[PDB]
Image 1 (cartoon, helix red, strand yellow):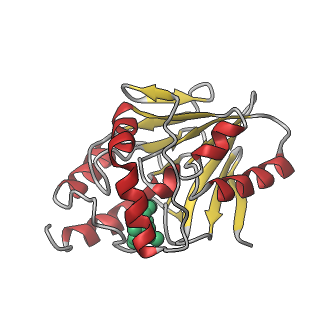
Image 2 (cartoon, helix red, strand yellow):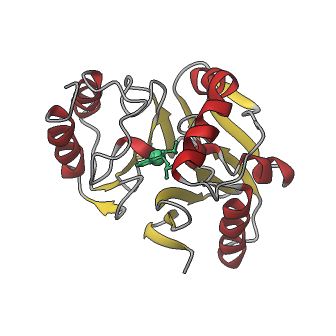
Length: 227
Ligand SMILES: CC(C)OP(=O)(OC(C)C)c1ccccc1CS
Ligand SMILES: [Zn+2]
Protein backbone atom coordinates (compact mmCIF):
# COMPACT_ATOMS: atom_id res chain seq x y z
CA UNK A 1 0.00 0.00 0.00
CA UNK A 2 0.96 3.68 -0.26
CA UNK A 3 1.00 3.76 3.51
CA UNK A 4 0.85 1.19 6.26
CA UNK A 5 0.12 1.38 9.97
CA UNK A 6 1.42 -1.63 11.89
CA UNK A 7 1.75 -2.52 15.56
CA UNK A 8 5.28 -2.76 16.84
CA UNK A 9 4.46 -3.22 20.57
CA UNK A 10 1.23 -2.70 22.48
CA UNK A 11 -0.20 0.77 21.73
CA UNK A 12 2.88 1.74 19.68
CA UNK A 13 2.52 1.55 15.88
CA UNK A 14 4.80 2.41 12.98
CA UNK A 15 3.69 4.33 9.90
CA UNK A 16 5.52 3.43 6.68
CA UNK A 17 4.73 6.37 4.40
CA UNK A 18 5.84 5.34 0.91
CA UNK A 19 4.89 8.65 -0.67
CA UNK A 20 7.81 10.57 -2.20
CA UNK A 21 10.92 9.17 -0.44
CA UNK A 22 9.80 6.64 2.18
CA UNK A 23 9.53 8.14 5.66
CA UNK A 24 8.55 6.29 8.82
CA UNK A 25 6.55 7.91 11.59
CA UNK A 26 4.80 6.66 14.78
CA UNK A 27 1.32 6.46 16.26
CA UNK A 28 0.49 5.88 19.93
CA UNK A 29 -3.03 4.74 20.81
CA UNK A 30 -3.68 6.06 24.31
CA UNK A 31 -6.56 6.05 26.76
CA UNK A 32 -7.93 9.49 25.84
CA UNK A 33 -6.85 9.51 22.23
CA UNK A 34 -4.14 9.21 19.64
CA UNK A 35 -0.69 10.83 19.45
CA UNK A 36 1.04 10.97 16.06
CA UNK A 37 4.81 11.37 15.99
CA UNK A 38 5.79 12.89 12.64
CA UNK A 39 3.12 14.73 10.61
CA UNK A 40 3.99 12.94 7.34
CA UNK A 41 4.90 14.55 4.02
CA UNK A 42 1.76 16.46 2.98
CA UNK A 43 -1.82 17.22 4.00
CA UNK A 44 -2.85 14.38 1.66
CA UNK A 45 -0.51 11.85 3.28
CA UNK A 46 -1.76 13.02 6.69
CA UNK A 47 -5.33 12.35 5.54
CA UNK A 48 -4.24 8.88 4.40
CA UNK A 49 -2.75 8.21 7.83
CA UNK A 50 -5.94 9.45 9.47
CA UNK A 51 -7.94 7.01 7.37
CA UNK A 52 -5.81 4.14 8.71
CA UNK A 53 -6.16 5.44 12.26
CA UNK A 54 -9.97 5.46 11.98
CA UNK A 55 -9.92 1.78 11.05
CA UNK A 56 -8.11 1.04 14.39
CA UNK A 57 -9.71 3.54 16.85
CA UNK A 58 -12.63 5.89 17.21
CA UNK A 59 -10.72 8.05 19.70
CA UNK A 60 -9.71 11.56 18.73
CA UNK A 61 -6.33 12.45 17.28
CA UNK A 62 -5.12 14.64 20.14
CA UNK A 63 -1.77 15.87 18.90
CA UNK A 64 0.90 15.48 16.26
CA UNK A 65 4.60 16.05 17.00
CA UNK A 66 6.91 17.76 14.52
CA UNK A 67 10.23 16.09 15.41
CA UNK A 68 11.98 18.68 13.24
CA UNK A 69 10.98 21.62 11.01
CA UNK A 70 11.38 19.69 7.71
CA UNK A 71 8.73 18.75 5.18
CA UNK A 72 8.79 15.02 5.98
CA UNK A 73 8.00 15.72 9.65
CA UNK A 74 5.73 18.78 9.33
CA UNK A 75 4.16 18.69 5.87
CA UNK A 76 0.94 17.18 7.12
CA UNK A 77 0.35 20.04 9.60
CA UNK A 78 -2.47 21.77 7.68
CA UNK A 79 -4.55 18.59 7.79
CA UNK A 80 -3.90 17.92 11.47
CA UNK A 81 -4.89 21.48 12.42
CA UNK A 82 -8.01 21.15 10.26
CA UNK A 83 -9.27 18.22 12.36
CA UNK A 84 -8.52 20.00 15.63
CA UNK A 85 -5.38 18.07 16.56
CA UNK A 86 -2.66 20.07 18.33
CA UNK A 87 0.60 20.43 16.43
CA UNK A 88 3.44 20.12 18.91
CA UNK A 89 7.15 20.96 18.75
CA UNK A 90 10.01 22.49 20.64
CA UNK A 91 10.45 26.24 20.45
CA UNK A 92 13.62 25.77 18.46
CA UNK A 93 11.78 23.69 15.87
CA UNK A 94 8.97 26.24 15.65
CA UNK A 95 11.43 29.16 15.29
CA UNK A 96 13.39 27.37 12.55
CA UNK A 97 10.14 26.47 10.79
CA UNK A 98 9.07 30.13 10.78
CA UNK A 99 12.36 31.34 9.31
CA UNK A 100 13.24 28.45 7.02
CA UNK A 101 10.03 26.72 5.85
CA UNK A 102 10.10 28.36 2.43
CA UNK A 103 13.72 27.25 2.00
CA UNK A 104 12.98 23.64 2.99
CA UNK A 105 9.92 23.48 0.72
CA UNK A 106 12.14 24.75 -2.15
CA UNK A 107 14.84 22.20 -1.34
CA UNK A 108 12.22 19.44 -1.20
CA UNK A 109 10.81 20.46 -4.58
CA UNK A 110 14.30 20.46 -6.14
CA UNK A 111 14.42 16.69 -5.45
CA UNK A 112 10.66 16.11 -5.79
CA UNK A 113 9.23 18.54 -8.35
CA UNK A 114 5.80 16.90 -7.87
CA UNK A 115 5.82 17.92 -4.18
CA UNK A 116 3.32 20.73 -3.39
CA UNK A 117 4.28 24.32 -2.60
CA UNK A 118 2.91 24.09 0.92
CA UNK A 119 2.15 27.20 2.97
CA UNK A 120 3.69 27.48 6.41
CA UNK A 121 1.65 25.88 9.20
CA UNK A 122 3.29 26.39 12.58
CA UNK A 123 2.96 24.28 15.72
CA UNK A 124 0.38 25.64 18.15
CA UNK A 125 1.78 23.87 21.23
CA UNK A 126 5.44 24.80 21.74
CA UNK A 127 7.68 23.47 24.50
CA UNK A 128 10.79 25.15 25.89
CA UNK A 129 12.30 21.94 27.13
CA UNK A 130 11.84 18.22 27.00
CA UNK A 131 8.22 17.13 27.26
CA UNK A 132 5.94 14.16 27.67
CA UNK A 133 2.54 13.09 26.46
CA UNK A 134 0.15 10.19 27.21
CA UNK A 135 0.63 10.16 30.98
CA UNK A 136 4.40 10.06 30.56
CA UNK A 137 4.41 7.15 28.12
CA UNK A 138 5.58 9.23 25.12
CA UNK A 139 8.75 11.14 26.04
CA UNK A 140 10.28 13.76 23.74
CA UNK A 141 13.79 15.09 24.27
CA UNK A 142 16.64 17.08 22.76
CA UNK A 143 20.18 15.66 22.88
CA UNK A 144 21.92 18.04 20.48
CA UNK A 145 22.18 18.75 16.75
CA UNK A 146 22.50 16.05 14.13
CA UNK A 147 20.57 15.76 10.82
CA UNK A 148 19.20 19.23 11.64
CA UNK A 149 19.98 21.52 14.56
CA UNK A 150 16.63 20.86 16.24
CA UNK A 151 15.67 17.23 15.73
CA UNK A 152 14.27 15.53 18.80
CA UNK A 153 13.98 11.92 19.92
CA UNK A 154 10.78 10.30 21.17
CA UNK A 155 11.02 7.38 23.60
CA UNK A 156 8.27 4.98 24.63
CA UNK A 157 9.42 3.55 27.98
CA UNK A 158 6.78 0.81 28.40
CA UNK A 159 7.64 -0.73 25.02
CA UNK A 160 11.34 0.21 25.00
CA UNK A 161 11.01 1.80 21.58
CA UNK A 162 13.11 4.78 20.45
CA UNK A 163 12.18 6.97 17.51
CA UNK A 164 14.62 9.55 16.18
CA UNK A 165 12.77 10.83 13.13
CA UNK A 166 15.32 11.69 10.49
CA UNK A 167 18.29 11.10 12.84
CA UNK A 168 18.37 7.29 12.72
CA UNK A 169 18.26 5.32 9.47
CA UNK A 170 20.28 2.84 7.37
CA UNK A 171 21.89 5.01 4.72
CA UNK A 172 23.70 8.35 5.13
CA UNK A 173 20.79 10.23 3.56
CA UNK A 174 20.47 14.01 3.56
CA UNK A 175 23.52 15.81 4.95
CA UNK A 176 22.66 19.26 3.52
CA UNK A 177 21.37 20.56 6.89
CA UNK A 178 23.51 18.33 9.09
CA UNK A 179 26.12 19.15 11.66
CA UNK A 180 28.41 16.32 10.62
CA UNK A 181 30.94 16.67 13.48
CA UNK A 182 28.23 17.08 16.14
CA UNK A 183 26.11 14.17 14.83
CA UNK A 184 28.10 11.39 16.56
CA UNK A 185 28.40 13.52 19.68
CA UNK A 186 24.60 13.67 19.79
CA UNK A 187 24.39 9.94 19.28
CA UNK A 188 26.84 9.43 22.13
CA UNK A 189 24.88 11.79 24.39
CA UNK A 190 21.83 9.63 23.54
CA UNK A 191 23.59 6.37 24.34
CA UNK A 192 24.91 7.79 27.61
CA UNK A 193 21.33 8.17 28.83
CA UNK A 194 21.26 4.35 29.05
CA UNK A 195 17.61 4.15 28.09
CA UNK A 196 16.28 0.58 27.96
CA UNK A 197 15.88 0.05 24.22
CA UNK A 198 14.66 -3.09 22.45
CA UNK A 199 13.60 -1.40 19.20
CA UNK A 200 14.80 1.61 17.24
CA UNK A 201 12.47 2.88 14.52
CA UNK A 202 14.47 4.41 11.69
CA UNK A 203 12.89 7.47 10.08
CA UNK A 204 13.88 6.43 6.56
CA UNK A 205 14.73 3.09 4.97
CA UNK A 206 13.24 0.00 6.64
CA UNK A 207 11.93 1.04 10.07
CA UNK A 208 12.32 -2.00 12.34
CA UNK A 209 15.75 -2.29 14.00
CA UNK A 210 17.38 -2.98 17.33
CA UNK A 211 19.53 -0.59 19.38
CA UNK A 212 22.45 -1.16 17.03
CA UNK A 213 20.94 1.13 14.39
CA UNK A 214 22.37 3.95 16.53
CA UNK A 215 25.88 2.48 16.24
CA UNK A 216 25.37 1.71 12.57
CA UNK A 217 24.54 5.30 11.68
CA UNK A 218 27.22 6.63 14.01
CA UNK A 219 29.89 4.72 12.11
CA UNK A 220 28.57 5.93 8.75
CA UNK A 221 28.51 9.63 9.74
CA UNK A 222 32.01 9.44 11.24
CA UNK A 223 33.29 8.47 7.75
CA UNK A 224 31.19 11.10 5.88
CA UNK A 225 32.47 14.29 4.21
CA UNK A 226 33.11 17.06 6.79
CA UNK A 227 33.48 14.51 9.64
C1 LIG B 1 13.96 18.29 3.14
C2 LIG B 1 13.46 16.88 2.93
C3 LIG B 1 12.66 16.36 4.12
O1 LIG B 1 14.63 16.05 2.76
P1 LIG B 1 15.11 15.49 1.34
O2 LIG B 1 15.83 16.58 0.44
O3 LIG B 1 13.77 15.07 0.57
C4 LIG B 1 13.91 14.68 -0.80
C5 LIG B 1 13.57 15.87 -1.71
C6 LIG B 1 13.03 13.45 -1.05
C7 LIG B 1 16.05 14.05 1.51
C8 LIG B 1 17.05 13.83 0.57
C9 LIG B 1 17.84 12.68 0.63
C10 LIG B 1 17.63 11.75 1.64
C11 LIG B 1 16.63 11.93 2.61
C12 LIG B 1 15.80 13.05 2.61
C13 LIG B 1 14.76 13.17 3.74
S1 LIG B 1 15.51 13.68 5.34
ZN1 LIG C 1 13.83 13.00 6.77
